[PDB]
């Protein structure tokens, strides 16, 4: 029986058998006052002490969120839906520690994604026990508020200041600083890692002065704050808050009185109205996301990045070969997960209008022109593949490359990866390729479990990636030094080398998507 005295009271964990060894798990430790009643829409409050023993023996509630039912019964989408009760009382975190208790272990803190509208730390592909077992690091993950409940912004109004979910994440980092030593962890060796909106959160913690001293290094998988979906302007943030107020019958002339009215609404009334706060949307719509609040974010983050105003440390950044394709089956005409989605030129043009609704006709013609220079113009997958690359390059790859270039210009080691292995267990069809989200299981080491029917080559690849991530967190350098691997070189603004990750041949290349990213980063903003 293992029990740990934290600064707020004793917690009891559970022992787990992983790979013929033991990992101790503390699931569902509270780290803030439940943000209920008058605390809804406020920054999270400090946790009042307790004198009993908290049984941290099961995952806690997930934060309120809509659950999309686009593919009912399909494991490809339902593996992402919350697997605990939805409650506003969701500010809990989880801790995996190796057995026996380590002496001074490096800590990896996961921040899940989900477009800032969904997500929970209890997903099976976020299970930190494999990493604890195999690399003897400590894994932490927290639940943070999402959607309106996490990001509604009446900016300057402390009743709804914005960025509440980001402050949830920060309060959890603060908990690790105060308490992880009691679990055998090293508060001075803390690496944040997250994917998608979680990766954008990680990059915002690099900009936030309150987070500076709460972590050492950062890993950004398929996301960064300069991605077009990742920050909502103050103009949209106020239009969306007032639209949500109109939809719930909460329009009041006193801005503080709107929030009082929204605080008496059921979570479901708020959730069912989150969709319609914008008149036009896309599959990458983020209706309630990070804002420049003057607190977590002191200025527009593109300015902070461009002028070197961020934590100076190492970063690991990367993207997957087919970031875009998942978004095509959530709205592009002619696309299906149940057929090969061969689309015509005309369907490609309608696809562009879906993803770029307020872009001029000339702007959409420029995208078409850049992306239809066929190698083989007889190839019938041509338009299907170009629309995927349009959405992936614009929304993830080019922003991540630009983040890494600007960050490394201020003298820090950066490492960039290109993940191009399609999981053999991937439930989505083959035309969707190496999808958004499907490197996570490799990072968390699920293919290390031989029972799970991943291939042998996939076990090798996961084993290698797990070591690289752990070596980055421990030593700031993501090498696999023992198995004659390819050496991962630093990403420099001039050569811009990156590592490809795959089963067959991990190799070094330069200037990923160079021509595409010139179009998106330099030309497309002008249209
Ligand atoms: C800012 O919001 C207004 C209002 O949005 C409408 O009302 C909300 C309560 C919600 O139901 C939304 O879906 C509505 O669109 C936007 O004004 C609307 O714009 C559309 C398209 O331009 C137009 O067809 C509607 O008639 C407008 N309705 C009203 C009441 O003005 C406005 O576009 C938003 N500003 C943005 C998005 O920049
Ligand atoms: C691929 O499928 C899409 C979606 O159609 C649905 O799924 C299919 C597997 C099949 O079971 C269809 O009967 C389903 O309706 C096809 O696009 C649809 O085409 C119909 C035909 O007129 C149209 O009414 C719908 O609006 C279309 N929906 C979308 C989202 O485009 C598409 O034609 C199929 N492509 C190929 C190459 O077979
Ligand atoms: O997950 C989200 C987030 C959202 C998003 C928006 C902007 C940036 C990044 C992500 C998204 C992601 C993928 C498709 C559509 C939307 N929203 C809930 C929807 O159920 C999407 N299902 C989640 C998974 C679908 C298949 C593979 C990817 C994950
Ligand atoms: C635990 O280790 C501490 C040193 O941590 C190391 O230095 C910092 C700057 C980071 O770069 C981190 O990655 C390193 O692991 C010691 O200061 C501390 O006294 C140690 N405490 C115990 C109990 O062992
Ligand atoms: C916590 O778990 C132990 C052992 O399973 C049990 O004896 C104890 O009563 C539990 N405490 C609470 C508050 O449920
Ligand atoms: C609005 O509500 C707040 C909260 O009680 C109050 O302080 C303020 O005086 C009210 N009136 C105006 C005009 O802000
Ligand atoms: C290196 O190779 C051995 C077998 O030769 C394997 O057991 C080990 O897990 C590998 N390590 C990494 C980090 O890939
Ligand atoms: Cl702004
Ligand atoms: Cl490619
Ligand atoms: Cl061009
Ligand atoms: Cl053609
Ligand atoms: Cl297939
Ligand atoms: Cl095909
Ligand atoms: Cl190799
Ligand atoms: Cl390329
Ligand atoms: Na390429």
Image: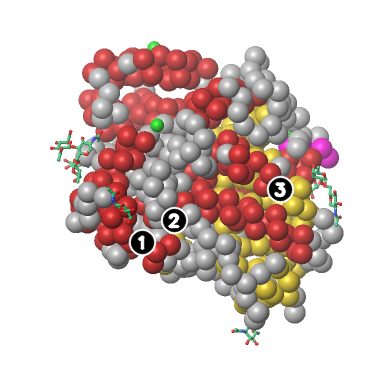
Q: Locate residue 234, reporting x and y percent.
A: 36, 36
Q: Earlier in the sequence, mark 1 or mark 2?
A: 2
* Separation of residues labelled 1 and 2 (CA atoms): 36 Å
Helix, strand or loop under label 2: loop
Instruction: Name which quarter of the figure residue 334 lies in.
Output: top left
Please, what is the dominant secondary structure of the magenta stretch? loop
Q: Which mark is residue 73?
A: 1
309 or 441: nearer the eye?
Answer: 309
Q: Locate residue 220, reporting x and y percent.
A: 59, 39
Q: Relative to residue 72, is residue 396 depicted above or below?
A: above
Camera-near label (1 vs 2) is 2
165 or 371: nearer the eye?
Answer: 165
Q: Identify the residue position indicated by label 2 in the image.
A: 42
| Residue drawn where x is 83% and y is 40% of the image | 482
**Is residue 331 left or right of 94 when viewed as pictured?**
left
Instruction: Name which quarter of the figure residue 304 lies in.
Output: top right
**Is residue 450 left or right of 307 when viewed as pictured?**
right
Helix, strand or loop under label 3: strand
Q: Give the range drawn in magenta.
A: 478-483
Q: Which quarter holds ligand 8?
A: top left
475 or 44: nearer the eye?
Answer: 44
Q: Relative to residue 249, is residue 502 depicted above or below?
A: above
Q: Which of marks 1 and 3 is nearer the N terminus?
A: 1
Camera-near label (3 vs 2) is 2
Q: Quarter holding the C terminus?
A: top left
Q: For mark 2, does the 10 Å Cα neighbourhood hold few (<14), some (14 to 19), or many (20 or more) residues? A: many
How many dots with numbers?
A: 3
Q: Identify the residue position indicated by label 3 in the image.
A: 190
């Amino acid at each position: 029986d293992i029990i740990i005295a934290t600064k707020n009271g004793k917690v009891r964990g559970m022992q787990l058998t992983v790979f013929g060894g033991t990992v101790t798990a503390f699931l569902g430790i509270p780290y803030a006052q439940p943000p209920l009643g008058r605390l809804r829409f406020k920054k999270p409050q400090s946790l009042t002490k307790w004198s009993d023993i908290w049984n941290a023996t099961k995952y806690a509630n997930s934060c309120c969120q809509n659950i999309d039912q686009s593919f009912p019964g399909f494991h490809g989408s339902e593996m992402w839906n919350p697997n605990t009760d939805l409650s506003e009382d969701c500010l809990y975190l989880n801790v995996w520690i190796p057995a026996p208790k380590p002496k001074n272990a490096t800590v990896l803190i996961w921040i899940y994604g989900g477009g800032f509208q969904t997500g929970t730390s209890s997903l099976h592909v976020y299970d930190g026990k494999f990493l604890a077992r195999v690399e003897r690091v400590i894994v932490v993950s927290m639940n943070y508020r999402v959607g309106a409940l996490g990001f509604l912004a009446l900016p300057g109004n402390p009743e709804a200041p914005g960025n509440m979910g980001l402050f949830d994440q920060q309060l959890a980092l603060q908990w690790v600083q105060k308490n992880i030593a009691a679990f055998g962890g090293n508060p001075k060796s803390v690496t944040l890692f997250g994917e998608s909106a979680g990766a954008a959160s990680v990059s915002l913690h690099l900009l936030s002065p309150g987070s500076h001293s709460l972590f050492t290094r950062a890993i950004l998988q398929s996301g960064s704050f300069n991605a077009p979906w990742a920050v909502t302007s103050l103009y949209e943030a106020r239009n969306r808050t007032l639209n949500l107020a109109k939809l719930t019958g909460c329009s009041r002339e006193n801005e503080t009185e709107i929030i009082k009215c929204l605080r008496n609404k059921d979570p479901q009334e708020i959730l069912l109205n989150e969709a319609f706060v914008v008149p036009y949307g896309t599959p990458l719509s983020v209706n309630f996301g990070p804002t420049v609040d003057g607190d977590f974010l002191t200025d527009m983050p593109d300015i902070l990045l461009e002028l070197g105003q961020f934590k100076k440390t190492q970063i690991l950044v990367g993207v997957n070969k087919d970031e875009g394709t998942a978004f095509l089956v959530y709205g592009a005409p002619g696309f299906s997960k149940d057929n090969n989605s061969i689309i015509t030129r005309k369907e490609f043009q309608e696809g562009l209008k879906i993803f770029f609704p307020g872009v001029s006709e000339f702007g959409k013609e420029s995208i078409l022109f850049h992306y239809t220079d066929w190698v083989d113009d007889q190839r019938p997958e041509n338009y299907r593949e170009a629309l995927g690359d349009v959405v992936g390059d614009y929304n993830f790859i080019c922003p991540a490359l630009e983040f890494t270039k600007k960050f490394s210009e201020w003298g820090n080691n950066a490492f960039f990866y290109y993940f191009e292995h399609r999981s053999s267990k991937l439930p989505w069809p083959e035309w969707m390729g190496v999808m958004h989200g499907y490197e996570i299981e490799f990072v968390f080491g699920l293919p290390l479990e031989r029972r799970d029917q991943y291939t042998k080559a996939e076990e090798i690849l996961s084993r290698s990636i797990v070591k690289r991530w752990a070596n980055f967190a421990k030593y700031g350098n993501p090498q696999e030094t023992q198995n004659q691997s390819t050496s991962w070189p630093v990403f420099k603004s001039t050569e811009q080398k990156y590592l490809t990750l795959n089963t067959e041949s991990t190799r070094i290349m330069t200037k990923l998507r160079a021509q595409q990213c010139r179009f998106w980063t330099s030309f497309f903003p002008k249209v």
